[PDB]
Image 1 (cartoon, rainbow over the protein chains, first blue to last red):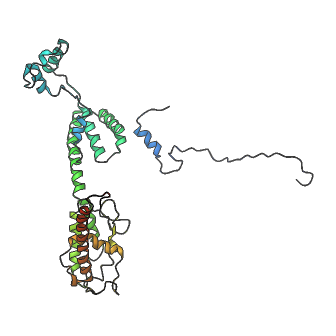
Image 2: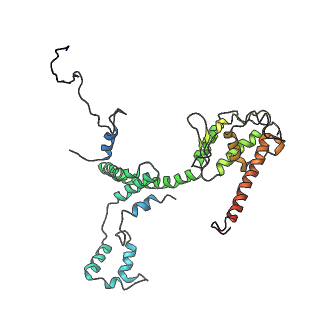
Image 3: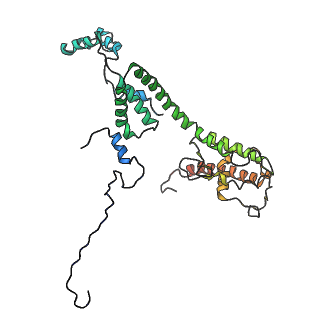
Length: 50
Length: 281
């Protein structure tokens, strides 16, 4: 800071702590109902997946 | 028409030549009764001339379930209950379902149901051709504004009759529509010529008002183009009560009946005049 300010580099980071990360299994990531569209496709798929 | 669902199941689930089903014909290949070629079976190599006799003398028994269920699935696809690309997983979903709970009871009511869906498919095309889904919607619209209560004349009764008549007649199924709010007639399914029928709030104060015949451009020349379109659309269903002096509406109807006449005689003479269609004049 000021007139005798030393050469410098920047550090950027973040926090969010009470949260837990989410990824919706939905064809777009919105909540369009409780039983998602991809969740129904996998019923009609009648098959096991790893 | 939409086909027979049980034919379109058998056609894609069963033997193309002789089966262990058509025993009566196999016993005319065998025995040389087949009048078109008696000696054909007599000339088969022993290797298949003998095994054919076995399957005719003691027939193989089979499980019919897959042909029953597919005759439902083909019906569900034609009646548009399911997308055509669901037919493999709807077939499988039913096959596991009816195999999980299999019994002589279930096997009988699948058979009952194969007749029912076959009839439902034949009925659905009637239910689209007869336009009844439009005639019910018109009959609902006629509850929305004063039925059997005009003011200046009861030519309103003839016009209401012309709607019912037209919507019964016109075979491209003129679609009456509840809209979100207002009722509409679409006419032909390509919709160009849609009328908003609750916007015959014009054609209220105009029943009985006499024609100002000398010039159409005058004080009472009100009608919105949506209302003129409804008159032009019904025009070929309207001589009853509409003769010129009966109203300005009667006069418009006498012009539009003849304007339609003019259009189709000018088509008859245009398709004549265009004989060469290419350079010769």
